Image (tube, helix red, strand yellow):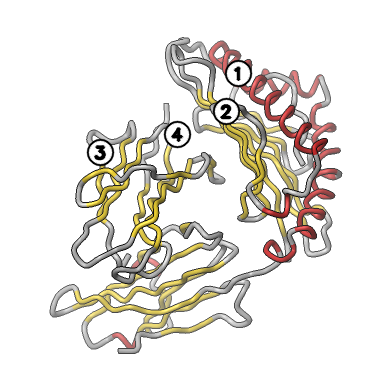
Amino acid sequence: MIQRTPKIQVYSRHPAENGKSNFLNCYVSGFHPSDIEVDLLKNGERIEKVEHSDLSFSKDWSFYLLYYTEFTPTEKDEYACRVNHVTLSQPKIVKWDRDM
Amino acid sequence: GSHSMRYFHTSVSRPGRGEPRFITVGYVDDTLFVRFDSDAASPREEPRAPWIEQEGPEYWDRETQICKAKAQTDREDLRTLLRYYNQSEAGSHTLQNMYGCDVGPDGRLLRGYHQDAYDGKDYIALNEDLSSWTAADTAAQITQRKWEAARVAEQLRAYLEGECVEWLRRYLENGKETLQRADPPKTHVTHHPISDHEATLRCWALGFYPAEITLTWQRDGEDQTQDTELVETRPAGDRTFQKWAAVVVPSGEEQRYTCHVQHEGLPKPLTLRWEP
Amino acid sequence: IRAAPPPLF
């Protein structure tokens, strides 16, 4: 049974500007099987009411999803995306970096 | 230019947790326009782009019937595959199906597709001839024999040459304001000190549509392929896409480094360099 | 517009 572990990108829709409203995205791709758990975190805690795209897949059959939420970035607030998948022995947390 | 229509389907069994979940989406180029999810409270195919909303009740009614019909055949196929592969009924399995067409600038068929994958592996695919099959293994060969016996490829060929092409043309016209507009990338180069001896130069493309783009770094005009970190092209959430390419550069050598951008929304490829 | 589903596997 083939398994492919997620690529994970965490990033904003628009270039980040402190105190300015934006969207926080977590894009998970290249994975199989399709069952996955994705949370967006604000200062280590899970943000509620996060939305996601409908399941679709690439030419190599691997899956991709986008998870997203409205956010207003600030100097000090830390954001992240936490991902669990069958391929991971523990959930992976990828920190938001405004330069990536 | 050239354009494509695709429908994507995925069924995932979940023994002990009800019937397989079925999700299908349709795209024209990189624009989602319809969706159906069997776990939705009252499942119907729903519009996801404004230009399809004008389609009438007969349209929506037939699309929803098809979605439900395909969901059911996927469920039966998933049972069949446990037999073909001598598998337990205990585990979760995945069936994926894609089909659609590619058309040129004049709208004529370039290529049609209809292909299936079980548990992330190729199962059976319609060949480019639209008349013959590639079966991945002796299991798929059983399906091939049945489908050859029922002349299934002829039926798909007729669709792919006919309705697929004709309705893609229709959608391209109805959604001309967006589907026929390329948004070029907004591009810039950033510099990120790593140590006293090197820094990262990151070449950004933002806000572009469609998704296809080439971002390259050269050093003294030699491509830096093996040395460039290229992130996957990623959706911004507003229809547009983003991408970046980065190189690690010895301090003082930044001007030997040029970023090259090709997008269909650009008249000429761009050349960028870091500007302190 | 969608195609009619093919036959069973």
Looking at the picture, do discs 3 and 4 lie on one chain?
yes
In the rendered image, which quarter is residue B156 located in? top right
Q: Position of residue B251 (x, y in %)?
A: 21, 83
Crowd band around label 1 with a 10 angstrom C-alpha radius: few (<14), some (14–19), many (20+): many
Q: Which residue is mark 2?
A: B22
Left-right relation of B58 to B52: right
Secondary-structure class at tag 2: strand
Q: Position of residue A40 (x, y in %)?
A: 31, 47
Quadrant of the image containing the C terminus of chain A: bottom left
Quadrant of the image containing the N terminus of chain A: top left
Left-right relation of A35 to B150: left
Q: Nearer the viewer, residue B105 or B25?
A: B25
Q: CA distance from mark 1 to mark 2?
A: 9 Å
Q: Earlier in the sequence, mark 3 or mark 4?
A: 4
Looking at the picture, do discs 2 and 4 lie on one chain?
no
Q: Nearer the viewer, residue B42 or B114?
A: B42
In the rendered image, which quarter is residue B182 located in? bottom right
Q: Which residue is mark 3?
A: A91
**Amino acid at the residue labelled 4:** Ser
Q: Nearer the viewer, residue B153 or B235?
A: B235
Letter of the chain that mark 4 sits on in the rendering:
A
Letter of the chain that mark 2 sits on in the rendering:
B
In the rendered image, which quarter is residue B129 located in? top right
The reply to whether dot 1 and dot 2 touch (C-beta < 8 Å) is yes
Q: CA distance from mark 2 to mark 3?
A: 26 Å
Q: Is residue B250 visible?
A: yes
